[PDB]
Structure formats: C-alpha cells, structure tokens
Image: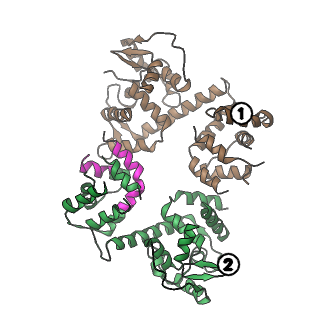
Chain colours: A brown, B green
Amino acid sequence: SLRKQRFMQFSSLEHEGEYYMTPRDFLFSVMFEQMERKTSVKKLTKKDIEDTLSGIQTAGCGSTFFRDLGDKGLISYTEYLFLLTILTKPHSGFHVAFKMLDTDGNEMIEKREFFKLQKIISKQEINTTLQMRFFGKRGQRKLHYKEFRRFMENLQTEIQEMEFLQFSKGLSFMRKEDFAEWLLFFTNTENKDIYWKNVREKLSAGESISLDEFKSFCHFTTHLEDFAIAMQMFPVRLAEFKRAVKVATGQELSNNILDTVFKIFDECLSHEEFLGVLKNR
Amino acid sequence: SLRKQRFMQFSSLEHEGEYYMTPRDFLFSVMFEQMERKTSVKKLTKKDIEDTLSGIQTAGCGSTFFRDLGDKGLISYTEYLFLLTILTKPHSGFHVAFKMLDTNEMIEKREFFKLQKIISKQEINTTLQMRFFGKRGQRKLHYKEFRRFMENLQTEIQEMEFLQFSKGLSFMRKEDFAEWLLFFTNKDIYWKNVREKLSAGESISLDEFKSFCHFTTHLEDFAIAMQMFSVRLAEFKRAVKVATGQELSNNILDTVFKIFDLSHEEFLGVLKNR
C-alpha cells in the first residue's frame, strides 16, 4: 500500500512490528515529499510513552500543538490517515460520522467509536497522542464534536503557518514572488512558463505579504464554488474582483495578493484559468 | 434551441414575434412530456395584461400560486428557463447572485432582467415582474421573499406530481410510489419484488411523499452516513434521521426496503438518476 509505504518511510518508532510516527515525523511527512532516512528505526520504550504523556501535558492546545509536542508523542498508521483526512477532506462528513457514532444524540463519542472511525477511513495495544488528547490520560472522557472540530481547525492553522514559513524561507514576511511561487506550485511546467512570463516582467516588489493575509487567501480558498459562479456572472477588473471575493467569501483581501494574482493572469483578469489552477490544490 | 422548441409548442400567446405561456401552460410544460397543440397560438391582447394583474391580485402567495393563476398571467421565455432552473438547480447560487446584484439585500427589476440573461446563457409586463416588483415595476425584492417563492414553487410541483401519481386521490398506494421511484430507471427484479412482497397496506400520505422529496436533497450526507456501516431498518432510519435531520414514516422505508432487497449504492444510484 503506497500510503503505508510513505508512512513507514517517515516513521521513527517501531514496536511489535507496527511502526509509529512522532509529531515531528508527521509534520515532516505533510511538509516534505521525501527526506533522507539517516537513522534506523529505534524500537519503542517506556520512556517514550511517558514522554507522550509529558508532551501533551506541557503543549499548547491550539495552532501550535504538534510543534510544541516535538518528539514527545505517538501516532499510529490509522491515526495518520485520520489526520490526513482532516487536512484533505471537508468537515461536514465528520459531523455526519459523529452523529452516526454518538449515543442519544449527544454529539459525543468514546474512544472505541474513534477506533471504528479510523477503521472505516482506513479500509476506505498502546495509547497514542490522539487518544490521550481527545479522551482521558486513561480514557476517562468522551470527545464532543465542538472540541474535535476546533482541533481540526487548529491543525489546519498549524499546517498553514508552517507552509507560510516554508515559502517565506524562515522570515516573517513573504515576497509577492514567493506567493506566486506558492500559488503555481502544483502547476506543470508549460503553464508555469506562461505565468512566469508575466511575473518575470511586470510583478514588482512592493509590500510583502503578512501571515494574516496568507491566511485570508486560505479562507478564500474554501469558498471557491460561490466565487466561481459569482465570476461566471461576468470585463472583470480589480474593483469587481474585490467585490466578488467580498460577497463570495466575506473577506477583504490585501492589495499585495490581488496585485500578484492579477498580474499572473493576463488589463482584464483571466479567472477561468485562475480558478482552474486553484481547484487543482 | 431545443428548449425554445419545447417552450414554443407549449406556448399559447404570441406578440411581435415573442411567444408567451400562461401559468397553466407552464404547469402543463413541467408535468407532461407532450401535449397535442389543439388550438392555434393567439395574439396577445390588453385583456391578457389586465388579466395578469387581476390574476396576481386574487391568487395565493404560497404553494398554490400558479394553480390559482390559471390562464390569467404570462411567462416569458427567459422567465421560463429561470423557473426551470429553480426546479432543477440548487438555491445557494441564487443567494450569491442576489448579493452580487444588490447595492441592501434587495434587487430591482433591471437586475432581475440581468439575472434572466445570465441564467439564460448558462416589452410587455409579465406575471413575475408584477409579482416581485409590483404593478409599477418600482418595488424591490428581498432575498428572503424570493427564496420563499422558490420553496413555494417547489412545493407546488411536488403536490401536482403527487396528484399525478396518486391519479387524483388523496393517498398514494405504495405501488404507485414505486411507480414514481422507478420511472426513469435489473429493472425487472425491482418490479418482481413490489409485485409479490409489497403488501398494498397503508397508503402514503402527501406529507410523507414531501418528506421523501426533501430527503432527496441530502443524498451526499446520507451516502456518508451509510458508509458508516462497514444494514438493518433501525440503522437506515437513524441514517436518514441524521443525514436529513428528519424522521421518516415507516411506510416509505418499508417500500424502499422491499424494492431494493434491503448494499445502498444501488438504491442511491436509482435516486440520484433523477
């Protein structure tokens, strides 16, 4: 299985024959396509489980959970597909799942139905970080959907921030050419040459994009259908683009981002190709 | 244009070269694949316009609007494609359209014309213009009002569809509900089960038909709620209850269960085919 092969090539721990990632290995696995396995896979010990407890115990509960965990944590393979589906699938399906797994419409599940959720997503021994975080140190607890959904949103925020620092190349701001590089990342070579013909010559360096403006673009990405039809209503210029994004997403967008995407896609915007490139990610 | 072909041979009025339906011609156009044009197309006169106004004045604003209108009203071609996509496309696009058209959560007549042009490519005053923008074309249409109009029209079409398959009566035997479900649809084995293991027991009420009809709109959520089982009647009823939010009468579930040999993918293949 290709997914499990990848999970294994990013796994640092092993026990009884089933490999485990660390939070650092998970972040590495979403952020880098490959990495040099310079060290063998050490086997799991009891200092590592106690480290799993301590890390949760001293980590932030928000957008810095996984980074604050560092190497103190464990993630099984099913939990890794689970987290992958948080980052790549819409959240309403999870609300449907919670409403089909809960007892007496309480919208709260215990640890066993969390196991069965990962079995269902999987086919489609020890206690891990997610079990200790959602449920008890000892399974004392049950996971309400509100808690779990703000966990999903926090993890998405985390991955967004680390993507920003990756394309900022460590610094606090992101030049508009690095935003253009990030937008056209999954585009093939031909179209990238056509767009880089535009950026190459008429995208200037002015302001540099903040993390919050990147996050604003990221919230605009989630309302692409409404925006797509609001565009199909149109001849489309910057005032009309800004209005269309403002009513299709509710979000005011920073002049740097609009300038960048307008000068990539050309005094009229080529929104057919713009949204074709967007929906590929 | 083939859609214009249909609109034209269902049209009863004409003017200046532009053909117009009455509300009855529209309903007939949604309910019957064909009809014999027995009468010629008449020229539009002023008694028809004042009849449109009066018909609007003495009609219900809810689920009986078009049937209460009868022949006293007119519907342009652009308005006919407009109403057709109201019945076959989701409604959120209309909300984004409204907020792309307003200066206030409200649209004027000019922007309604714009909307019928955009929906079209996707002189006289008609029924919809007088209803939304008044006799005088100077009113404004709030999105809530118009969404009430869409839901009321869908209710209307549901009621007339029920009366079509109930064949005039107040209740619908399970066999005619199966007739409606399998209309556009392996087809023999479905008809083998309704014939021998469907007990023409209770009859399906109109409200339970409407419940199934609104369940049809949450088919994706239901698909995931079904993929959670990885089979029985309580589990199917729970899945419909959380996928649509809404309790369903045991009568319909019995019918759909014995039609489809209680593997839900095939059932939803038949459903999403309409």
Please report the residue visible at 46 percent of the width from the left and 35 percent of the height from the top: A86
Q: Nearer the viewer, mark 2 or mark 1?
A: 1
Q: Is residue A241 left or right of residue B165?
A: right
Quarter of the figure with the C terminus of chain B: bottom left
Can residue A121 be seen by looking at this rendering? yes
* Residue B19: percent from left, percent from top: 60, 78
* Residue A161: percent from left, percent from top: 59, 30
Q: Which residue is mark 2?
A: B123
B218 over B24 or under it: above or below:
above
Q: Is residue A207 left or right of residue A8?
A: right
- Answer few, some or many: residues within 10 Å of disc 1's Cα (few below 14, many 20 plus, some between 14 and 19): few
Task: Output the chain of dot 1.
Answer: A
In the image, which disc is placed on residue B271? none
* Label 2 element class: loop
Q: Which residue is mark 1?
A: A193
Q: Depth check: B158 or B64 in front?
A: B158
Q: Which residues are magenta?
A: B212-239
Magenta-drawn stretch contains B214: yes
